[PDB]
Image (tube, coloured by chain):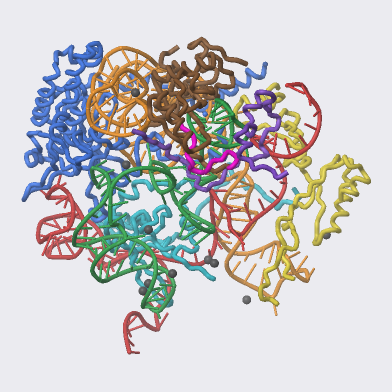
Chain colours: A blue, B brown, C yellow, D cyan, E purple, F green, G red, H orange
Amino acid sequence: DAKSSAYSSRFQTPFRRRREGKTDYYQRKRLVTQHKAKYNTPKYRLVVRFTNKDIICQIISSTITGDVVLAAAYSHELPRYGITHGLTNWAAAYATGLLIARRTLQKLGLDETYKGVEEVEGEYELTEAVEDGPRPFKVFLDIGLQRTTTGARVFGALKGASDGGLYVPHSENRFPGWDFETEEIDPELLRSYIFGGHVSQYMEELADDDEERFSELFKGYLADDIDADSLEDIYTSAHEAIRADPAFKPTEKKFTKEQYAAESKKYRQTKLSKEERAARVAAKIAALAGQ
Amino acid sequence: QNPMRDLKIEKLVLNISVGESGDRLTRASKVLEQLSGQTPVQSKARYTVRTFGIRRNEKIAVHVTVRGPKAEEILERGLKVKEYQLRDRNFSATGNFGFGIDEHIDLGIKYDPSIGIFGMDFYVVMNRPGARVTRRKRCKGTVGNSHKTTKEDTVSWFKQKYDADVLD
Amino acid sequence: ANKYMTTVSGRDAFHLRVRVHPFHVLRINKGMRGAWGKPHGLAARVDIGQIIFSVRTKDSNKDVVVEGLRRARYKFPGQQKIILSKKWGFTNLDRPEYLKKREAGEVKDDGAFVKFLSKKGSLENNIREFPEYFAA
Amino acid sequence: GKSHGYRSRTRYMFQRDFRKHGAVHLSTYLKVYKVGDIVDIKANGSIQKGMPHKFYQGKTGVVYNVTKSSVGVIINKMVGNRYLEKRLNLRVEHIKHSKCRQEFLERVKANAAKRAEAKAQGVAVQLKRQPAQPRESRIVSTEGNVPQTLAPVPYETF
Amino acid sequence: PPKEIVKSNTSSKKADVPPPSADPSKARKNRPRPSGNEGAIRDKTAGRRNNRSKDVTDS
RNA sequence: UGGAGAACAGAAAUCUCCAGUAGAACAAAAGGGUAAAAGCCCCCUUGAUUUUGAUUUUCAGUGUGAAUACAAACCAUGAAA
RNA sequence: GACCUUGACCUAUUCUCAAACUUUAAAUAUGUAAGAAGUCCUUGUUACUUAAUUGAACGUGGACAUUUGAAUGAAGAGCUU
RNA sequence: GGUUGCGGCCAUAUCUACCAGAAAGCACCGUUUCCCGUCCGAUCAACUGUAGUUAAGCUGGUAAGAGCCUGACCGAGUAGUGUAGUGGGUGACCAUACGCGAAACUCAGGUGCUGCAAUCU
Ligand SMILES: [K+]
Ligand SMILES: [K+]
Ligand SMILES: [Mg+2]
Ligand SMILES: [Mg+2]
Ligand SMILES: [Mg+2]
Ligand SMILES: [Mg+2]
Ligand SMILES: [Mg+2]
Ligand SMILES: [Mg+2]
Ligand SMILES: [Mg+2]
Ligand SMILES: [Mg+2]
Ligand SMILES: [Mg+2]
């Protein structure tokens, strides 16, 4: 930007998280409310959020106190499974989706019962329930404020979670491969995207036309000696490793909570009492008293 | 001082308010189409007037928004007609500016008698980096006071880069 | 009340404020089928203790003002009383209170009325508006 | 002519509170109602579906049925010289758990403890509440509190 | 291949009534007024196309 | 709605930025309700469907009208809840 | 443009009002509760519900009884034609 | 303690003006082959974390700041009001008795608290 006292007085603030521009409450209501004759059965959202630089997948349920994380999985983990690059791309989104699925089913003790798709040919299928045995763990995709488009990464993480054995109800018409005219999916194209085909094809095409740019982008691929054709083998080897040991393993933590806090305390400004506040006014009138 | 607060063109908007709705409006559309190299957009009347001879929803005026390099080009072509001389009046309090041309031939188009002649409004929107903050979906903020574009600031920039005068 | 005060003391010797505005519309019918009346005139609703008229003057001119208000009473129905205020003019301050606030710089003229320094709000804008305070 | 529609005379009753318009907060939807629960009915004017008739505003009853979006409540309405049972289907946004009951249960619990504690300790305990009693005797000293004499004040004008 | 895009309305107003800015009393009277040759071509209704449309008086 | 800008263009045409708690709109009275909507624009549609019961208002606790929440189907939409 | 002056507009003040205005907001009147049809423990049934050996509803068996869960009253209480 | 994701309550959290911000995060920021969307790669989509930057966003602090919140035997036991009299008064209205009891005002204080998960000199 002035605002009159009357304007200020009558103003109704949005909810904090609507002010912060993070939560869509209209969506949230429809996601979280359970059927009232299911009592304290929690609904579980697969929350998927892209920062720049990171993918966050969390399985969350609600409570009046606040939401409660069942499991989580970040793309910055994926180095542990041998993906060091493109950690916010479509292929990583799939991998993080696969990781959260495999990690959750291990925690619920349901991972032998529901393997998933181990093959991965880019085929539309939900996890079918086992006859005479527990139903699959059901979660709903919560994409937050992200826009729904055909080929967006957020349905990549969905595909990964479905393929990992979570029941995640979905349709096929927002995967890369959906032909809008004939209204069918092309499994080949979806399959390519799962193994970073779109990235590989681009490295091939560009390490050819504009070799100047291929060094600027893809500097990290050159530096580690990764040709375009190896990408499919990275992501294949990554999936296998994810499925073998999905269990979460935290960072070691140089320094402790109290140590971290001590360091940060030193950069936080503190409030000025009420006596200090008074003294500063007394000093300010004394300045304008002379002149 | 910081490179992240260096002005640029957000966008240039070319506007032709034809009064009529019929033939002359479709001719003006052709002019912007060849100039911009983009399919332009037609605006409809907000309400009937009578003296102007326009009706609610009539479909007068056309415009087109250009960004990036072709904004810089089309702006030059436009400032050649003005002889690199804008008035101080032409700069808005929010630090955008605009001028107008009679006759679109002066830009550099072969005449063609079927189309005819058209004036234009050039309107140039300035911003710094980080203007995405106001425009994006999630965590939509406002630009801090220090980072706002100003009349003072835009004028200095226009003089310095283009080597132009600002009158009165 | 005006006429009398202007004759015996002169038109600039007092300020007279009428403190009641007739906002209530009276109806008049003019058989009892369809009897809701039409607007007839206007009237002011006054309570017990409610000020009808106020006059400020110099203290010299008490007797005149009291007489002019006494003359006005005959135009109204009911009982009215004529009261000498403890306050300074049309302000809400007892005469000593106002004087102390004026000896300090805490009062400034605002046409016919007055603005008071509050010990509240921005310190900068107070010092614009009340220079003579603070200076001490 | 006269007018007696379903929401006649609700102008103020179904208004939102000042500065409390807009979306219903989520805790309203995470509350769990069970048959037998005692609830208080208070219409949210922002939710036009499942809305109680104005008569039930401020009435308390018992949940008898639970469905997807809603609860069935029983209310006793006086009609003539007798109470009829009414059964209402309310969306949960117009209902809240009565704290009357919540604070009765805390007493049932507290009484159980006291009664157990009393048997094992081996004595006898009073579990009924009593009305507030007449004050017992007390000595009030005048140390630093000598009585201060007041008198009625004369009339002044202001 | 011709094509026609129209700007979508964001306004709520759907009465064909001009705003309260549109007030003839608010017109500024102290205007330049193009005089001379300037005014000649700018003044519409000052040509043969205008005259040739008007019907002739019977005097 | 207001402000500041842009050939003809003016109080009113169209374009742009800033401010804007709703001061707008929501067929039709008035009241209530609504802001990533319940408003505006766009996409897809026929839940304005089938089968009968229960319930609220008016009340005799009859009818009619209107409305509420479920059930059993079959559908629409949406990545989904 | 230069000023002297009257409406308009803005800012800070000022006098006075509302059945069909309102941030606030009584008194009186008004719904519900104050227990054995309760409470706690234990573990049966189901085609409902759960990712589930989860719940939901109804049960078995067990435990707690006059200070059994405020006051005052109760001329009997309830039911029918 | 900081930061992020998802939150609860929904201004003690908002608003205006200034100043500060290690680390990490977040962000702005680079690119247009691919899916995708636009009058316009601005928004939306994808790709790279590579070229750059704390300028803005964000977080905190400042203000005899505006707003908001809390309290007060502050105003005020005032206004109003339940009950009572073969009380007063021509009336309008008023006083008293046994009860209940505001709002404005004034002054004082305050200015987000907190849950789950991950991360950080
Ligand atoms: K009289
Ligand atoms: K009926
Ligand atoms: Mg949505
Ligand atoms: Mg009526
Ligand atoms: Mg309806
Ligand atoms: Mg009936
Ligand atoms: Mg009817
Ligand atoms: Mg009543
Ligand atoms: Mg870009
Ligand atoms: Mg800074
Ligand atoms: Mg009597």
Vertical order, G63 against C104 (above or below)? below
Q: Residue at x 69, y 43 (%)?
A: E57
Residue at 52%, 24% (x, y): give it: B94
- Horizontal side, residue B87 vs residue F75: left or right: right
- Whether F57 is drawn above or below B132: the answer is below
Nearest the eye: H83 or C57: C57
Which residue is more in the foreground, D2 or B49? B49
Residue D19 located left or right of residue A83: right
Number of numbered discs on residues: 0
Q: Position of residue G64 (x, y in %)?
A: 22, 62
Q: Is residue H73 above or below residue A277?
A: below
Q: Residue at x 58, y 18 (%)?
A: B87
Measured as percent of width and height from the top left, residue D24 is found at 38, 48
Against B38, residue D131 (above or below) is below
Give the quarter the ligand 7 occupies: bottom left
| Quadrant in the picture for the N terminus of chain E | top left
Q: Is residue C102 left or right of residue B79?
A: right
The residue lying at 36 percent from left, 55 percent from top is: D96
Residue C121 image offset from top left, x and y in percent: 60, 31
Q: Magenta stretch: residue B58 in it?
A: yes
Q: Is residue C63 visible?
A: no
Is residue D1 visible to us here?
yes
Quadrant hosting residue A99: top left
Question: Which of these two is toward me, A203 or D95?
Answer: A203
Start and end of the magenta stretch?
B50-62
Main SS, magenta residues: loop
Front in this rendered view, residue C121 or F36? F36
Question: The C terminus of chain E lies in which quarter of the figure?
Answer: top right
